Amino acid sequence: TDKLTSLRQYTTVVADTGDIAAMKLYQPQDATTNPSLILNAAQIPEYRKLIDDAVAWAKQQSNDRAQQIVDATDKLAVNIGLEILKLVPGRISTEVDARLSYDTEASIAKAKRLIKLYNDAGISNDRILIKLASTWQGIRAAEQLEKEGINCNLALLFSFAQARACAEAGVFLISPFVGRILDWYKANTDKKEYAPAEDPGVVSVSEIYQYYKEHGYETVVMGASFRNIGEILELAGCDRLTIAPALLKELAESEGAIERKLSYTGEVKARPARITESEFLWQHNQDPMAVDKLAEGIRKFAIDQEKLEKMIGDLL
Amino acid sequence: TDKLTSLRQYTTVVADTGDIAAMKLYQPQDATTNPSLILNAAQIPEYRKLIDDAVAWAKQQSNDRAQQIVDATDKLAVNIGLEILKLVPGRISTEVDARLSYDTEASIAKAKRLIKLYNDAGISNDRILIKLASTWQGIRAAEQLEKEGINCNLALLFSFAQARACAEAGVFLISPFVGRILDWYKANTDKKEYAPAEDPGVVSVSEIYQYYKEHGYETVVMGASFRNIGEILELAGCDRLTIAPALLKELAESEGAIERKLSYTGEVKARPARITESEFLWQHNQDPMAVDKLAEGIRKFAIDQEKLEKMIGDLL
Image 1 (cartoon, rainbow over the protein chains, first blue to last red):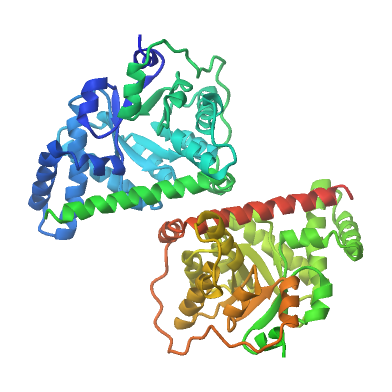
Image 2: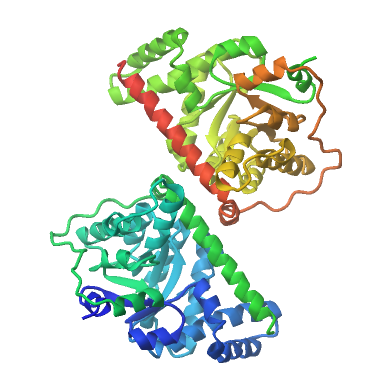
């Protein structure tokens, strides 16, 4: 058989795109989106109807142009998620405005607003994951949201300190960014080529996976952002993996069964005391790669958010 | 006349070293030290007596080896400052353990401990500046200390967000790191050579200086960490400048008067509302250079702190 089919025996497959065409082709269980993917998806001609509906709906909610742009941009992200939910049996991840990444209160409010839009469309919370950046503020926001019945996807996770803090907060799921970790090492290190087993991103997710299973944490581990299928195969066994259409295609076209790589067969160990903000900050900042990438990821998503608002603005 | 003498007409000269030999040669008003300089100073043979006194004193304060190492390391930094105060009429800057940079409470306690050691030696607070890293936690610590009569030197300042937060906290003085800003641009940018006037570090300090004088902030602006005398000359007029002995030598050996570069001749403008933690974090992290350098600076100072403790440990 092919790699994609074989991978499904050990890992839940998730598609990383806002394009419904991939949902039909690969039949993933869940789907993930982010500001950059939503921006690209808005370029898709067939998605024109989703944009028009969003704008129309927004103009019917208020007469304030400022609020209309916000309502239209949020509704568009929700409309795309709604189309995807028609093709997948699992969940859709929708990301909150990245500009609120360092504001716990504003992030909680925004998350509840998105949940509201999905609920107004008849979709219940169990089909959604609100995606936020894994800053200390984002984690604190998520801890609160989970208590109120809103499951979260903690993304842009790079350091072990972030992983630990997320598990202790009891979040539904985490998305460590494998490929971006590799990117950093290629650019800031002498070594430019890595064997799959030595890929920094792979090693990072593997250690996180072990730490989580070893202590009985229920937080789902979902590797994300890949550069090649080698990273994916090396993580076979990870709870879930969200993969871009291009890599999904390569897996489906390659023959040969694969073997499970990630497993924890021991018994559960006792959990340590919770890490504090001070310890979190010290440990996170001890990681040059994590320091750079977390801040950078947030900057890029914020820019894409602004570009989308610009686009919507010219339609009002 | 020479450059050094001319510079003194517009700017207060400060020596950046723990070596008393430079104090006698350049007669600076104040002197600054940091963990790296304290470590180097401990290598100076004539400083052997200062180390022995520190160790002896520590063993007389307690019988706990753990506490002795801490007492010995703090006393050594204070002993070096005490030697310098005999040669300078102004202040000495002594830095708190960098490992506490993200812990407000621990930083306040450590600062008070150092103040205690100086007071036990008969030195009053007006001759000292407690130096801390400009993280949000360090700034909050400083705001509290200033209220209790302890003046601070907010260092490792890179972003405008840090500068603004420091002025609003009412700190006694800030130390923006000019040379390290240049280092980042040389390494992460295409352009490797900068004219003094276009030096990123110089432009940064100039904008900070303007912002401070324009709003009537009393916080002293002291440019620090230089790579060449060009940066120094381009900042003539800055409240103070702390310069390494090597650059101090170059200024003294070069002939020719210099002209004042930094000045604010307008009237004071009203101050804006205070920046919040969320806004501070968003703005600071918008600066790729500041993100990298602040975290890196703290990492290096922490390592030097550990090396000093190692050294002291083998003497107990």
